[PDB]
Length: 52
Length: 54
Length: 53
Image 1 (cartoon, one colour):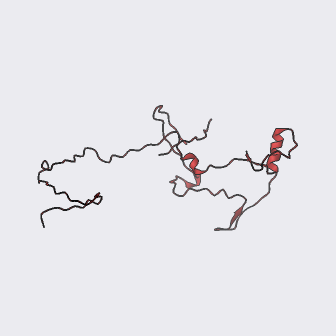
Image 2: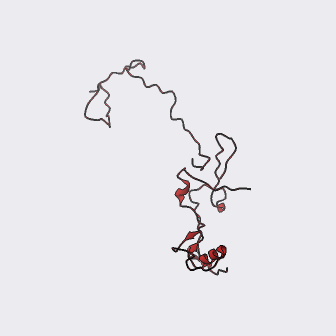
Image 3: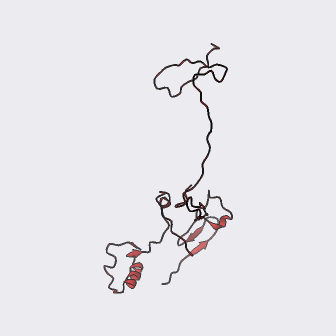
């Protein structure tokens, strides 16, 4: 309707909808995902067999 | 060495075990086992790599 | 003992002989591919001595 942003839960378990609110301000949202560190790679190998 | 035929040395009268073995190679009772490993041998992580020394 | 046998190379594909060895290096990034095979280095995480194979 030009009003609600609709998203599809591609893995929905049954059949449902959830209506939620999100304000323009970052503090106005109910739940806050606040990343600190992301996708930092690690590298190495095992000296007994040289497999990476 | 690896055995090709059951009871290697069954027909080798040679008493000197070293020579009896040379005979087993010649007569195809036993084959030298030296060979490359199936690739999985070193992929299990439960692996042993022959040392090189000096 | 004594063994006699054949090694012949006519060209392109017509390669004949008793045992072909035929090493596999494709996909392995080599400095002078004529070398065949490659080195790997780890270095122990406890003792800090190097390790190579």
